[PDB]
Image (cartoon, helix red, strand yellow):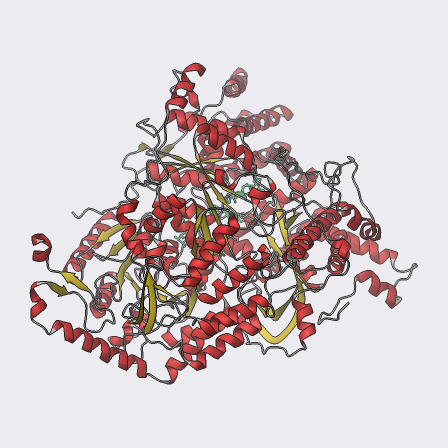
Amino acid sequence: TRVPLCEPEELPDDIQKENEYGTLDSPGHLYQVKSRHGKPLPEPVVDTPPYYISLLTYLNYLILIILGHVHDFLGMTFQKNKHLDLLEHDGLAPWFSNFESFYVRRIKMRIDDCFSRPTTGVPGRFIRCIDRISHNINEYFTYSGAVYPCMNLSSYNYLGFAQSKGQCTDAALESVDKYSIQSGGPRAQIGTTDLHIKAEKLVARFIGKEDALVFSMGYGTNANLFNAFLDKKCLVISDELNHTSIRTGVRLSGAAVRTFKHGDMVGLEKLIREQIVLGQPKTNRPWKKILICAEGLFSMEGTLCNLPKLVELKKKYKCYLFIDEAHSIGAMGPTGRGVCEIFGVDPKDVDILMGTFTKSFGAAGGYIAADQWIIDRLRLDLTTVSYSESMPAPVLAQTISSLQTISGEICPGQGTERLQRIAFNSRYLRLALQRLGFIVYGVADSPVIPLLLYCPSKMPAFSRMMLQRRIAVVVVAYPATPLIESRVRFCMSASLTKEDIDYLLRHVSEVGDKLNLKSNSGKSSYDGKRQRWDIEEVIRRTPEDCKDDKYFVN
Amino acid sequence: DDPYRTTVEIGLILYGIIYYLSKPQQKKSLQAQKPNLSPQEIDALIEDWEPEPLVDPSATDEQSWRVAKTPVTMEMPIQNHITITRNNLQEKYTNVFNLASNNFLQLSATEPVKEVVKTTIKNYGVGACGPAGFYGNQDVHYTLEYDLAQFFGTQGSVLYGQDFCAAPSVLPAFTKRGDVIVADDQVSLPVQNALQLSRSTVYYFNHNDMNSLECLLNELTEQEKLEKLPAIPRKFIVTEGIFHNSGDLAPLPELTKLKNKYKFRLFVDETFSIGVLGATGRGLSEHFNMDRATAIDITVGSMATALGSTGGFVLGDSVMCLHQRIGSNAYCFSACLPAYTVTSVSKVLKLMDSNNDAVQTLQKLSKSLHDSFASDDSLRSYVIVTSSPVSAVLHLQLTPAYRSRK
Amino acid sequence: TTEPVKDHRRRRAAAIISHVEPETFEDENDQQLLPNMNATWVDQRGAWIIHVVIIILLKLFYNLFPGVTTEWSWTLTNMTYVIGSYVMFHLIKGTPFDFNGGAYDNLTMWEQIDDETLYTPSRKFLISVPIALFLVSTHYAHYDLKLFSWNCFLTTFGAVVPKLPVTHRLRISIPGITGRAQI
Amino acid sequence: QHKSSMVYIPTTKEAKRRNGKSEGILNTIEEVVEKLYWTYYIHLPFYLMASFDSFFLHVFFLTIFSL
Ligand SMILES: C[C@@H]1CC[C@@]2(OC1)O[C@H]1C[C@H]3[C@@H]4CC=C5C[C@@H](OCCC(CO[C@H]6O[C@H](CO)[C@@H](O[C@H]7O[C@H](CO)[C@@H](O)[C@H](O)[C@H]7O)[C@H](O)[C@H]6O)CO[C@H]6O[C@H](CO)[C@@H](O[C@H]7O[C@H](CO)[C@@H](O)[C@H](O)[C@H]7O)[C@H](O)[C@H]6O)CC[C@]5(C)[C@H]4CC[C@]3(C)[C@H]1[C@@H]2C
Ligand SMILES: CCCCCCCCCCCCCCCCCCCCCCCCCC(=O)N[C@@H](CO)[C@H](O)[C@H](O)CCCCCCCCCCCCCC
Ligand SMILES: *Cc1c(COP(=O)(O)O)cnc(C)c1O
């Protein structure tokens, strides 16, 4: 009835090191990416399944919605004593009403076993999971205190910096020995140390800006950044697929919001022109300023933003640009600088650059980079700096070690191998999956490979069947996604090797053949012919051909 | 007659055709709104528009002095005796006596805790690599949640990644348009942000005044009774344990009596009172010798001020926590805490359970500090003291006469 | 009485006929910040043939029982489709998923379709389908005006009447028959 | 290579071919039945439902076929 505390396992050094990070097999399994030099980015193309799949999806959702209301009505009307949470006891309203919790109770409840799974130990290329047994219908669980390893394709460690034995761990332990774990307070009265300024300058030099700021949390950074310089008389133009933190920050700021469709620039230009002409509502006076918010790389889709067009538009119409890049600051680029490196765009064109250390550097926190005359004002106008706690010492040490490793200072040739490994793994997996006959999204280099499952009842079967094979995956669905399109999101890491990918390919091929999940058309291959290759031929021929940049449609 | 039935069909078909032939129109129309414009004219408007600078740089040199005055500690943990430098290494001081630290009990610096952190770092790594929703939640987090719930006498608890963003993510979750909130006259900034984001009616009553609260509650009750609304809405009272800016405490028993009489819920934000108030240090409720499970409904706390590690927590019953695990924005879309923090805080809680010397020593020191300044006569004409004898922080204010004269 | 600093109070109608008050600046920002998911799925792929498939299946299942009469079967399938459409579109007000604050607490889905833009192709299809069904039912088999008048009355007042622009943003509250509606 | 602490789960085809379970005379019918059952069960909501409602829907489909 309670989560047991698991005793650590005692193993020799080599076995644990292999569990955390995998050794390379052959030096031919590396790939070095090349710059784009500014050539235009083509419009993405998406494949579609047949009609009957969509019709069945519509019928499934309709039946589920009808039955949910039938049960809700009958149970609320007759059996009152059982449902005491949703009724007022003595002049006090319930914590929540039945209507807003309909989706959680009626459809999501039957799937609660595939969402939250306790684990233990360091998340590497093999993750240890706690075994649990379900009672009633996912109401409560009973734990037998047994653990077993699984392959993880769901954790945010792109460069494999999550280790228990390494230079970063040594630096963290030394920092703990030198600086205590406790801080003083807000970074305006006490709590600033030389390590903070060192990290500031290191991040500023690594990005390419002139000055920066470091915060202890990323969500708070976004939620508190916007109100410092925006007001009711300003306008914010943002995409329709931005993160929640940006939405909360803009809501707190109080400015007006206009949104444009994903990937459309003609609509963006038309919206900018119209908004400039019309002016403020009900008074038709000109706006004080206009700001453009976008994201470097979108995790739900695995697609890039067309930065040069945004820069051109902001130069022509005299607007400001804000770029959010947390998934692409360390894992993408010829040297890992970010989205500004692949396109060749000068960093000075963008106004504000933000990112977090959680995804790639193995430590928690976030930052912001801009010009000197902006940072000087912001250090005074920000509310995080003078009201909230400061960043601890071990996290700073880990971040500094990771940054100096990637930059090539502390160790000669460790970061480049990681970049090449992650690039090759992503390309190989995407090409093999597309040659099998599935449907994937991406731009041929993103670490996110979303494979689409359309029927509502196929996601739990896929999750459970992959668990039985000792593989851990994460599946998302409504409303986080469009109603028709559900998907499973793969997060590729540098710690995995090629044989693991072959094992995964065999198992996923068998499961997809069983569940009828592979439905491909001619719009996904370069020759225009639907392809269903046998597995051994795929394994034999894909790793050599994945290097050429012509086999990929987008 | 038969032609009447055909005429009905004709009338339906005609309206269908008429609606089909029409063109789309929207209230939020395009440039054609005014329009009274031509392509040549629009370019003039576009070119005439001039923007404002992103930030105003006029006054930065006037406030740079406060940036130049920030102390910095070099190569040493923040402790009682430190060495500081100011104004970018131009001036240096040594053997400084620190009276600005915000850590009260100083239990995190002892040897028995420094081993739990090292072992945890060796066995787990530094940072978690996933959200609590998918795969990030581990066994140590559950252990800390159970320990907090057992220690503070509440059914459950929820862990947050930072204490600044706890209230603005909890309070809006349980309120909607059409609800009432009664807040104190002066509250801290995070509570103000929560109230702004809550999107509900807000009423204010005078500071530490019970007559005003009673009168306003009676007026609201009478108006609601006269309104005859079919569904009862939610009601909350927002206050603070020990105020951040003035260092004064709130009277709990009167609030409990009023909330029981007028059917209101009580929300208490106690960041500066968790580790210092009470004989054992269990919070505000222990000071007045009352049960927490009935006196208070929602509690917001911080682990940084007294316990000595980053994070925050919220205490409540089972339904609240179960709904909070899905309806809270800062909880869902964020990564989990590192393991060494939670292990160290659990060890500190066990140490607090073992012995209770630090609380007594701190209370004695605070009483001495208050009496020393509040017992003199020379400073009667210059400054006044706005803090309580039990607070660990002393606040000083200039006399209103001095402010006007100077 | 004491005046709140920030007031967001729901107000109900006070007359037999009334209209909902236009939204404010903050409400407009709240609605524009996040796309609505209840009204987006109508325009997507495969969302139009579904009604035809439902009609075809309802005809077959009601005709399957030997004891039914063709006129009665078509009237019953009209009952089913009209009642289902009225319940889904015009009866229920609100959003199952939670938006910022109250948000779309006062408008129905038909009002939420396509950001309140009128004369959209989806609206044309949704208003044309019941008419085509009615004419097909009338012409298909023999009928008598007795049930025919009531059937066309129900088709008009349950499917056609709510779709007119005159009834847009409109609320009717009988003093006792129907509860008061928030404006 | 280097050994690790992972336990590999064999695939279905390998287990079947190493178990000698495959028999041409009396396995094609079983495979056909398996395909017919799974295709019927997956593409239609039985897997997120309750036992009473699932049984009711099974009886409904069975009666529809029988009629
Ligand atoms: C073969 C056979 C044939 C026959 C058959 O079986 C098969 O065929 C079957 C086919 C069935 C129908 C299928 C589909 C529906 C739609 C459904 O849709 C409800 C959705 C609405 C809510 O309904 C739920 O919640 C209600 C909560 O009151 C429940 O009501 C009371 O239920 C109990 C007493 O009945 C007691 O507990 C209490 O007295 C009270 O809870 C109700 O039962 C429950 O359903 C959503 O809309 C509202 O949302 C808010 C509610 O939260 C309202 O309030 C808000 O108002 C302001 C906005 O203006 C906000 O600002 C304020 O903050 C805020 O207060 C808002 O006004 C309004 O829009 C209503 C039921 C119906 C017609 C079914 C009937 C039964 C059948 C005929 C079966 C049948 C057996
Ligand atoms: C003796 C015999 C006498 C016969 C008497 C006849 C009596 C007729 C009884 C009618 C029973 C059915 C009436 C209501 C059943 C359906 C009502 C469901 C409404 C529940 C709440 C709706 C909330 C909408 C929010 C929502 O989740 N929206 C969407 C997603 O975001 C939604 O989830 C999806 O888009 C799916 C809906 C699309 C499926 C196509 C439906 C179109 C045709 C309707 C015909 C209904 C026929 C029923 C057999
Ligand atoms: C992952 C994600 C976050 C998460 O914030 P943390 O507090 O660092 O976990 C923030 N911003 C973006 C864009 C993200 O994708």
User: Residue B84 is drawn in which quadrant?
Assistant: bottom left
Quick check: A405 left or right of A368? right
Name the one closer to the observer, A242 or B255. A242
Name the one closer to the observer, A25 or B360. A25
Identified at 60% across, 45% down, the residue is: A301
Residue lying furthest right: D25
Identified at 40% across, 81% down, the residue is: B351
User: Residue C32 is drawn in which quadrant?
Assistant: top left
- As drawn, B61 above or below C45: below
Spot occupied by residue B405 in the image (x, y as percentages of width and height): 7, 53
User: Residue A161 is drawn in which quadrant?
Assistant: bottom right
Q: Is residue B276 at all visible to an observer of this figure?
A: yes
- As drawn, A133 above or below C125: below
Quick check: A416 left or right of A542? left
**Could you tell me how many numbered marks the image carries?**
0
Spot occupied by residue D61 in the image (x, y as percentages of width and height): 69, 49
Identified at 58% across, 76% down, the residue is: A6
Spot occupied by residue A74 in the image (x, y as percentages of width and height): 49, 55
